[PDB]
C-alpha cells in the first residue's frame, strides 16, 4: 500500500546493498535512502554517497551535443569524419558514411577503424553504448577541451551540481558489487561519456529539476533541452515497441510524455523517469547491477499514476 514498502521490497528482492531513490510530484519531493554504501566497513548509504550513472551519463553527453548545435558549432547532419578523421567504418565491402545523428540516435550499426557495421547507418535503431563515446570525442574535437571540462563548464557548474563529475579516486563513492550466488565486490577513459559520469542523489534531483523547469533556464540551455527530447522517428519500430530514442533519453507518448533511461554498469545500476505534464521526476541509484532497479522507476510511476504497482 505504501511508497516506502514498494521501494524497500524492491531493494530486498534485488539484493542491492545500497539504494537511493528520489521522487517528486507537483513540487512535493521525498527521498528514500536505504542500506549500506560499503558492506565490509558498514558505511551507511548517506545523501553524500556517490554513484556511477552508467547509461544515464548519456543524457549529459547528449545535452552538451545539443548545446553545441544550438550554438552553431555543430550539426546533426555533419559527417563524422570531420571530427574523427581516423575512424572509417565498413558495411558489406563498402566504406560507410556516418553522421553525428547516427551516434546520438543509435543508428550507426557499430558491432574503431577497419570495422564492419551491423547494417547501413540510419537503417535501424540498435542500442550501442559506444555511440556516446564517439560523441564524447566529438565534443572534445569541437571544444578543444576535455570531456570532463566541457561537462563541468557547460552543465554542472551552471546548474550547481558540485558532486557530479565526468571522470577522466573519489571519496564518498560507494563500493560496487556484482551478483553470483552471493555478492562479490568488484570495486576506462574512452568510455566515460557513455557510462562514467558519477553523481549523488541530491545532484540528480537538481538535474531532474532543471529538466522539469527547463522553460525558466537561460535560453541556450532551454532550447537545447527541448531538442534533447526530440525522438528520432526515422527508424523501423517493432510491433510492441514504438518508443523513440532522443538525445540520451527514451521517449514514450503512452500515458506520456514519459521520458526515461536506465543505467547498467558492471557494479552499479540506476533509472530515471520524468512525466513532465504532472511534474513527476523519479530517480533511483544502486550500488549493484540488477534488472529490477531498471524497472523500479516504472513501478514508482505506476504507483503515482494509479496507486498500484503489483
Image (spheres, rainbow, N blue to C red):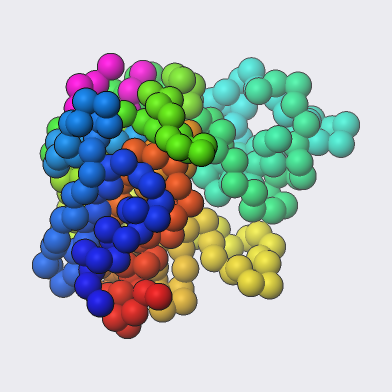
**Residue 103 versus residue 303: which sits nearer the camera?**
303
The magenta segment: 164-172
Residue 214 in view, yes or no: no
Q: Where is 53 relative to 87, above or below?
A: below
Tell me where residue 303 sits by quadrant: bottom left
Instruction: Say which quadrant the N terminus sits in.
Output: bottom left
Tell me where residue 56 sits by quadrant: top left
- Residue 16, horizontal then vertical, whole percent: 36, 44
Main SS, magenta residues: loop
Question: Magenta stretch containing residue 169, yes or no?
Answer: yes
Instruction: Say which quadrant the C terminus sits in.
Output: bottom left
**Residue 37 versus residue 101: which sits nearer the camera?**
37
The residue under the point 88% across, 31% down is 93
Could you tell whether 48 is left or right of 285 in the image? left
Residue 257 in view, yes or no: yes
The residue under the point 52% across, 44% down is 104
Question: Magenta stretch containing residue 90, yes or no?
Answer: no
- Residue 186, horizontal then vertical, whole percent: 43, 25
Amino acid at each position: 500500500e505504501r511508497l516506502s514498502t514498494l521501494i524497500h521490497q524492491r531493494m530486498q528482492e534485488a539484493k542491492v546493498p545500497a539504494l537511493s531513490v528520489s521522487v517528486t510530484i507537483k513540487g512535493v519531493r521525498q527521498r528514500f535512502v536505504y542500506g549500506v554504501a560499503d558492506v565490509a566497513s558498514q558505511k551507511a548509504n548517506t545523501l553524500d554517497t556517490v554513484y556511477e550513472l552508467g547509461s544515464m551519463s548519456k543524457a549529459f553527453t547528449g545535452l552538451v551535443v545539443q548545446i553545441l548545435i544550438q550554438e552553431g558549432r555543430l550539426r546533426q547532419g555533419d559527417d563524422i569524419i570531420t571530427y574523427l578523421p581516423e575512424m572509417r567504418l565498413n558495411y558489406q565491402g563498402k566504406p560507410a558514411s556516418l553522421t553525428v545523428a547516427d551516434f546520438l540516435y543509435h543508428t550507426s550499426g557499430l558491432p574503431l577503424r577497419n570495422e564492419n557495421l551491423l547494417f547501413a547507418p540510419g537503417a535501424k535503431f540498435s542500442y550501442a553504448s559506444a555511440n556516446y563515446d564517439v560523441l564524447g570525442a566529438v565534443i572534445e574535437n569541437v571544444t578543444g577541451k576535455t570531456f570532463t571540462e566541457v561537462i563541468a563548464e557547460r552543465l554542472t557548474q551552471p546548474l550547481g551540481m558540485s558532486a557530479t563529475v565526468a571522470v577522466k579516486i573519489i571519496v564518498n563513492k560507494a563500493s560496487g558489487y556484482k551478483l553470483g550466488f552471493g555478492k562479490p565486490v568488484l570495486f576506462a577513459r574512452n568510455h566515460v561519456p557513455a557510462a562514467y559520469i558519477h553523481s549523488t542523489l541530491p545532484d540528480m534531483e537538481i538535474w531532474i529539476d532543471a529538466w522539469l523547469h527547463r522553460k525558466a533556464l537561460p535560453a541556450t540551455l532551454r532550447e537545447a533541452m527541448s531538442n534533447s527530447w526530440r525522438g528520432n522517428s526515422d527508424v523501423p519500430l517493432a510491433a510492441d515497441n514504438r518508443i523513440l530514442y532522443a538525445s540520451g533519453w527514451f521517449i514514450d507518448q503512452n500515458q506520456g510524455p514519459y521520458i526515461s533511461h536506465g543505467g547498467q554498469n558492471p557494479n552499479f545500476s540506476s533509472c530515471i523517469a520524468l512525466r513532465p505534464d504532472q511534474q513527476i521526476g523519479i530517480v533511483a541509484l544502486a550500488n549493484m547491477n540488477s534488472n529490477l532497479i531498471l524497472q523500479l522507476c516504472a513501478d514508482i510511476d505506476n504507483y503515482l499514476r494509479i496507486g498500484k504497482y503489483a
